[PDB]
Image 1 (tube, rainbow, N blue to C red):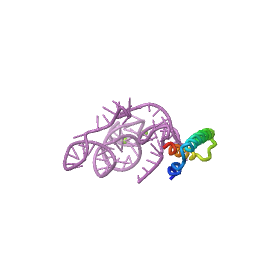
Image 2 (image 1 turned 30 degrees about the vertical axis):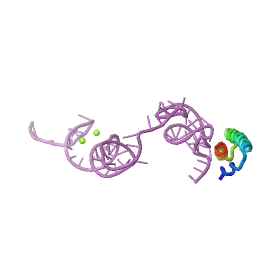
Image 3 (image 1 turned 180 degrees about the vertical axis):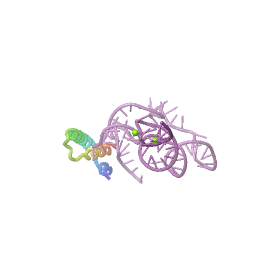
Image 4 (image 1 turned 135 degrees about the vertical axis):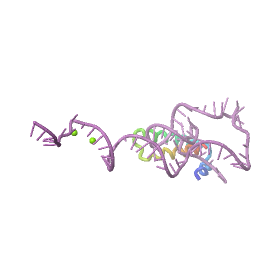
Length: 55
RNA sequence: AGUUACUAAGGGCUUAUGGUGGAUGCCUUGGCACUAAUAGGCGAUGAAGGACGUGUUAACCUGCGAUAAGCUUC
Ligand SMILES: [Mg+2]
Ligand SMILES: [Mg+2]
């Protein structure tokens, strides 16, 4: 499902996605280390989407 | 003058009960010996075996490898 949508995307847009998700993942981990992450599942969702984009 | 019981500090015997202990009996996600087939290898495209790390999850075990408790396709 999601893999089909990313396949529709071009390569340059995909690398923009990966750098943006890397930044967001860093922010989520820092907020968790400060006890300010209400949604603790977005870390896992970010990592899976990151892994899928890498595939 | 004569023959005399009671005593139980404690102990002995019988029976009953309580406590420590895990013998006997019943059972087992475990072992042993084989039968009928399959197969008889992995590695410089990095092996067998380990260290480290990975959780929204204290440690340990298991899974996994910076795509890290999982990624794609049929
Ligand atoms: Mg007495
Ligand atoms: Mg007595």
